[PDB]
Image: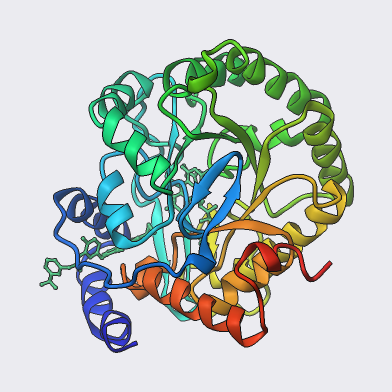
Amino acid sequence: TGDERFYAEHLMPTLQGLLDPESAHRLAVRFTSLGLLPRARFQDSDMLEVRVLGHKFRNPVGIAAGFDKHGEAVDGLYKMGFGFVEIGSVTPKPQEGNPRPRVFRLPEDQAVINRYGFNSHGLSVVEHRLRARQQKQAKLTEDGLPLGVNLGKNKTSVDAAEDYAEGVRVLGPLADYLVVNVSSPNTAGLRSLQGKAELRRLLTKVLQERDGLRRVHRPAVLVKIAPDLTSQDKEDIASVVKELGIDGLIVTNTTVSRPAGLQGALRSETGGLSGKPLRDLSTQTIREMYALTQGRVPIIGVGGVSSGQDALEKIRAGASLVQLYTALTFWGPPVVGKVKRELEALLKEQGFGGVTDAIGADH
Ligand SMILES: N#Cc1c(Oc2ccc(F)c(NC(=O)Cc3cccc(C(F)(F)F)c3)c2)ccc2nc(NC(=O)C3CC3)sc12
Ligand SMILES: Cc1cc2nc3c(=O)[nH]c(=O)nc-3n(C[C@H](O)[C@H](O)[C@H](O)COP(=O)(O)O)c2cc1C
Ligand SMILES: O=C(O)c1cc(=O)[nH]c(=O)[nH]1
C-alpha cells in the first residue's frame, strides 16, 4: 500500500492535476510502450490461475479495451502485472473519433465520463503491429498471458457486420479471443446491435468469417454488452449467445445513466460513465446474465474494479475473469498488483481452493 498510497495521494493527483484527462491517458499509453514504468515485484500464487475460452490465464485480472485502442503498449501492460491484455476497439478503416474534449475526470466519485467514439489507427496498421510481435505473444500465451482483440465499426459504416467480419479476417489469427463491441454509447445506434434479430444476424456473419480460418488461428468470440438493458434485452442476448454457441460474454461496457448523488462537477457531460458508480450495476448485470446462461457461458466481469474485494464480488456473481481501466486514472499502475494481492487475501480468508472455486459461488 506504501507505493499504492503514494500514487493515489501524490504522483497521480499532480499528473491528472497537471494535464487534461486525454493527454494524461495518451501519456500513460506512451510511457507504457516506452517501458518507463515500475517493475511489479508480485509473482502470482498458483491460486489465481484460471482456464477458460481454452486458455491459461496466469491471473484473472486483465486490462479493459479502450486504454491501448491501437495495440501500441502490449508488453508494458503485461509487465504492469495484468494476467491478460485486451486491445481495441479497432475499426476497419482508421478514423479521428469525436472531437476533444472527449475525456472528463469525476475526481469526487472516483469515476470518468468518456466519449472517444472509436478513435482507431484501423486493422491495416494494428495488424502490422501485432504481426511484428507475432512470436513473443505466442510464448506469452502458452506461458499463461493471452491477448484479446476488441472489434468496432467506422462512424459511417452502413452494415457493421461487414466491418466486424473484416476484423475477424485481419486480426482473428493474431487474437487468442475477439470481443464484438456492441455496447459503446459513443457511436451511432451501435447499442441497437444488442437487439435479438440484429445480434443473431451479426454474430452469425462474424462466426461465419471465424469458422472460415485455420484451427490454430481460431480465436474465442465474446460479446461486450452495456450495463443499461431492459429485463427483455438481457434474456434475448442470453438466448442468442447460447442459441449460437458464443464462447463467452463481457459485462459490462460504460453506462449512459448518472446514479443519483454524483458529486462530479462534470457529471452532465455526454458519454459512458466508467469507475466507482458503475461497480454495482456491472456486478448485478454479471449476476443476472449468469442465471440466464445457467452458468454455462464464460463471463469476463469489468466495471468499477479498483480493489481485491471489488474483483471477488464479480467472480462470486459469475465472473470467470475480471478487467479494470478507470481505476488506473486514480490508483496508477500499482492498482494491478493491489487487486491481485487483496484477492489472494479475501480468497484464503473465506477459504477457497483458488479462484475457479469461487466462480459464481453467490449462486
Ligand atoms: N496506469 C496509468 C496511468 C498513469 O501512470 C503511468 C502510466 C504508465 C507508466 F509507465 C507510468 N510509469 C510511472 O509512473 C513510473 C515513472 C516513470 C518515469 C518517471 C516517473 C516520475 F514522473 F514519477 F518521475 C515515474 C505511470 C498516468 C496517467 C493515466 N491516465 C489514465 N487514464 C485516463 O486518463 C483515462 C482514460 C481512463 S491511466 C494512467
Ligand atoms: C476512456 C475510455 C475508453 C474506452 N474505450 C473502449 C473501447 O474502445 N472498447 C470497449 O469495448 N470498451 C471501452 N471502454 C470501456 C471499458 O473497456 C470498460 O468496459 C469500462 O470502462 C468499465 O470498466 P472500468 O470502470 O473498470 O474502466 C472505455 C472506457 C473508457 C473510460
Ligand atoms: O470509443 C469510445 O468512446 C468507447 C467505446 C466503448 O466500447 N466504450 C466506451 O465507454 N467508449
Point out residue 293 in the picture as x, y percentages from the top left corner: 83, 47
Residue lying furthest top in this view?
212
Point out residue 77 in the picture as x, y percentages from the top left corner: 31, 54
Between residues 196 and 216, which one lies in front from this camera angle? 216
- The residue at the point 82 percent across, 30 percent down is 196
Name the quadrant containing residue 333: bottom left
Image quarter where the N terminus lies is: bottom left
Tell me if residue 156 can be seen.
no
Name the quadrant containing residue 86: top left
Between residues 326 and 84, which one lies in front from this camera angle? 84
- The residue at the point 58 percent across, 74 percent down is 310
Point out residue 301 in the picture as x, y percentages from the top left corner: 62, 57
Q: Is 344 drawn above or below residue 140 in the view shown?
A: below
Image quarter where the C terminus lies is: bottom right
Between residues 79 and 280, which one lies in front from this camera angle? 79
Tell me if residue 233 can be seen.
yes
Q: Is residue 325 left or right of residue 245?
A: left
Name the quadrant containing residue 71: top left
Q: Is 220 drawn above or below residue 326 in the view shown?
A: above
- The residue at the point 26 percent across, 40 percent down is 72
